[PDB]
Amino acid sequence: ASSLKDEVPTETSEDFGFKFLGQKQILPSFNEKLPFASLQNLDISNSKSLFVAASGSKAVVGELQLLRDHITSDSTPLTFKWEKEIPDVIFVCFHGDQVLVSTRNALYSLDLEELSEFRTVTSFEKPVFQLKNVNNTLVILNSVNDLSALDLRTKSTKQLAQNVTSFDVTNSQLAVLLKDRSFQSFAWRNGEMEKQFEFSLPSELEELPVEEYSPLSVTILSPQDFLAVFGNVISETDDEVSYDQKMYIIKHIDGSASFQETFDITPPFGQIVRFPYMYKVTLSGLIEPDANVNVLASSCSSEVSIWDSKQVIEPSQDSERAVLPISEETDKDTNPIGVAVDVVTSGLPLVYILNNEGSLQIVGLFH
């Protein structure tokens, strides 16, 4: 049923580029010891004009205009509204008038109107790898490969799926990557789901042994496309590290998925031990009415890619590529631990990217 097609091609575009707005250490470094989970340690609320960020055991909520000005000029110091030392944070995000903070072992709430209140929401029976917030629900992937749903209004928990190694959600879809390397997609509506479609790997891809090319990651790019990654399985504690990964764009047309390789999305040259996770920011309407540009980055890479809905886009010149810095301390490549979009500050949408070293980069994506 599933087929392997030709390499996805790369367009050189003279209409796309990044403008490097600036970079500064705003939080303490992880010194190369990061929590073995997918990390989402930066969020931005354009309505409130605020950000949360967590690096090196320090979590903060702060004013967005301040962070912008701190990074882009050299005259305004970074102060915060709230801060707390929390060791193992993997997830940070605004929800209503609250900020959710999650470690591997527990979820926490900070009340944005009474900052004195830092509540435990819940504990997890087993360590967690990934969390996504959709509306009033938190979708949680377990260390035992159990996909579950937390209602934020009622605190009750549903069991969604099993044997999952990666998942992704939008407002209306839920995708799942399984241990057997098969895929599943569901229509999603406020905790509720109905199987949309299902597929296995193409014959020529099963040829690659599961042990060498393990299921690492899914990303919904559109209701029809996915981006999947397969690669070596990495251990919680290992000093030395090399990543070997294969990326595929899956377009599902009429009961048949096609897979296609890229070598141009997020090449995994990383040298810090990281749990595999694909960062995605969506800018709908940056080209046209059914066209959302997706900016992509990886826990295992220093490069930032662009997907235009149909192919990968390289800017026509080297100053126009978004890349995360080499460390001034270790001389190693850094990777993102959070990514977020700023639409409201004053001086194109602005992509904020947070390091494994607490450094934050602002990059304007133009035309």
Image: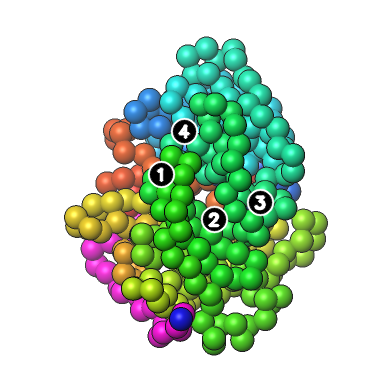
Q: Secondary structure at mark 1?
A: strand
At x 42%, y 75%, the residue is 257
SS of the residue under disc 4: loop
Residue of label 3: 146
Question: Which segment is the magenta one?
Answer: 2-18
Foreground tag (2 vs 1): 1
Disc 1: which residue: 189
Residue at the far front in the pictured view: 194
Q: Amino acid at mark 3?
A: Asp
Q: Which mark is residue 167?
A: 2
Tell which circle, 4 or 3, labels the residue nearer the N-terminal end: 4
Against 158, is 250 above or below? below
Q: Position of residue 17 (x, y in %)?
A: 31, 59
Q: Residues within 10 Å of mark 3 (few under 14, many from 20)?
A: some
Q: In front here: 8 or 241?
A: 8
* Amino acid identity at mark 1: Arg
What's the distance in space between the residues labelled 4 and 3, CA to CA? Answer: 20 Å
Location of the C terminus (image quadrant)? bottom left
Q: Is residue 213 left or right of residue 340?
A: right
- Using the rendered view, name the quadrant where residue 54 is placed: top right
> Mark 1 vs mark 3: which is more N-terminal?
3
CA gap, disc 3 to disc 2? Answer: 11 Å
Disc nearer the start of the sequence (2/4):
4
Q: Is residue 177 above or below residue 47?
A: below
3D distance between C-alphas at marks 1 and 4: 11 Å
Foreground tag (3 vs 2): 3
| Residue bearing the label numbered 4 | 136
